[PDB]
Image (cartoon, rainbow, N blue to C red; front, side, top):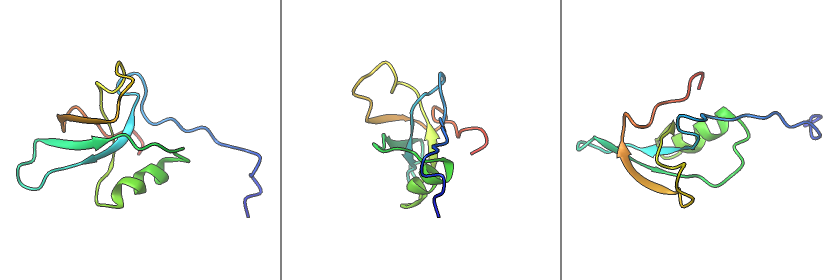
Length: 88
């Protein structure tokens, strides 16, 4: 039972470098860039957004360019630009 219904553990995935968590959908053969789209929701923890991405077969990543842009949603970026969070 959620006896911790009154306690909420804070969990922030990536900050400063990318500051934006999301799922990067890799390509098939023409790999080079991954379609990463910002997932609007309250990431309860790591296993939460880690699975939210793996749902379709993706993974939790962190990229840039989605900080200085209020409209940070869908972007076209390099796979290297999105580095997996440490400890994930």
